[PDB]
Image (cartoon, rainbow, N blue to C red):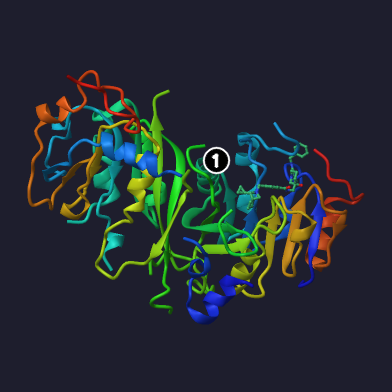
Amino acid sequence: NDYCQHFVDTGHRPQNFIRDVLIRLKDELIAKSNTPPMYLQADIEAFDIRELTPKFDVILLEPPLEEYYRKCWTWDDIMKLEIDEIAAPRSFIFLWCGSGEGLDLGRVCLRKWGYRRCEDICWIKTNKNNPGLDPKAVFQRTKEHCLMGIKGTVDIDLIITEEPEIGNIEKPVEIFHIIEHFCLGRRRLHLFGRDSTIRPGWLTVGPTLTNSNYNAETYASYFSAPNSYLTGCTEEIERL
Amino acid sequence: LFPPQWICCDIRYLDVSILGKFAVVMADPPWDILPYGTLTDDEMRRLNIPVLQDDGFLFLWVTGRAMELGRECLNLWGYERVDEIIWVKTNQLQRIIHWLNHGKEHCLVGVKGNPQGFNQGLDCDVIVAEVRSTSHKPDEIYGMIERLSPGTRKIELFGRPHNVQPNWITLGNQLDGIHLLDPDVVARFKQRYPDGIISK
Ligand SMILES: O=C(NC[C@]1(O)CCCN(c2cc(NCc3ccccc3)ncn2)C1)c1ccc(CN2CC3(CCC3)[C@@H]2C2CC2)cc1O
């Protein structure tokens, strides 16, 4: 059957009909090596990002785009973030780009900060619960893209969930699972996270956080020797 | 002229100015990502896509580093990218087939000029369909393109015999000969190629 024609006939998106959408020990290893959650309220447009130390192995960047809303950040604002100043020489970025011009401007940003794109992770949104509009659009936009970039020398590239209710800007928590399963290292930064996204193993920095516990010296002590190079998927280093 | 038409040719060398103007272009290029039929990045840049449309849409299949190179070509050829279709690949029971396994293929959607009378927003930007023979694009894309722009002339570059469709002219070097039915195209073809040969 043609699910595109079906969508035209019924308003049910084709992704509504995708079905079914030994790693547990590895999730347990991730959980064992996770640093305590750490978080900082900061107005990222006015904040010297260099105060965030040490340099990060993974950056998840989730700027609040205007298209998310039926303080917004333009790609002008995002491009001027000085991400290369806090990324480790070998490191990874995950940039939520939305569904419109961000698919191009987000790639400009990755190159500006010294990354090359190595994956395009698509969040496919179903409308099972409510079967059934940018002026440039040719098609109804039913997905968002998270670009993964790399700099320096188990999972699929799809996330499928029901489209959240209007005014809900949260991205699927599955993106954290994909990132952590890569075992890229333990210094993990989420820019534009919220109280609701704080997570063990992550430093969350955002303007709407209600509380902070970030201390640069304490944070760095989580990665001091013998722990400096752990992937975040290996067993803790024995002390005492 | 509605029935399928095609031209076996090296698309690097065909004079596409004889084909007229099209509401929709689709290309599935042999990007250099070399294997037989591949075009270099420069050959891709130099394709005379700009003569093929005044106002309409371009559908450009991309993978790997052609996600970026295809954006470069689209812009060099005079298009703005305004959508990106993904085809989620499934088996006959609707289950999904370097850092991640790949469940999808990507098709950029570019616009040139300011098209009028198209039916934008009828379809969504996700295709869910079976891999019906490896390396083929899903037939669903022709349906979405026809609902978008019904009855208009369309041209496909780097297609194969299974791709020929009504309202479409298909170009590719594995098509069987030259089959042209539109009198405007037939006239300009004989004028340009009196002895049927397409060289240099
Ligand atoms: O099989 C193909 N296409 C027919 C040719 O016949 C095959 C020889 C090349 N080809 C030409 C090449 C040409 N000039 C240059 C030349 C150089 C050297 C010798 C001879 C010619 N002129 C006219 N056709 C065209 C073909 C097969 C696979 C793909 C890959 N996508 C299928 C895909 C859609 C969803 C999955 C994926 C896309 C990226 C996401 C593209 C293709 O295109």
Chain under disc 1: B
Q: Which residue is mark 1?
A: B64
Quarter where residue B66 is shown: top right
Is the CB of mark 1 within 8 Å of ligand 1? yes
Quarter where residue B161 is shown: bottom right
**Three-letter code, disc 1:** Gly
Residue B49 location in percent, x, y? 63, 50
* Residue sticking out furthest to the front: A240
The quarter of the picture where the N terminus of chain A appears is: bottom right
Residue A202 visible in this rendered orientation of the protein: yes
Residue A177 vs residue B137, the one in the foreground: A177
Q: Compared to B64, does A196 lie above or below?
A: below
Residue B33 location in percent, x, y? 61, 35
Residue A169 location in percent, x, y? 26, 61
Decide if residue B111 is on the left or right side of residue B24: left
Residue A117 vs residue B6, the one in the foreground: A117
Decide if residue B120 is on the left or right side of residue A110: right
Q: Secondary structure at mark 1?
A: loop
Q: Compared to A70, does B131 lie above or below?
A: above
Quarter where residue A217 is shown: top left
Residue at 17% across / 38% down in the picture? A36
The quarter of the picture where the C terminus of chain A appears is: top left
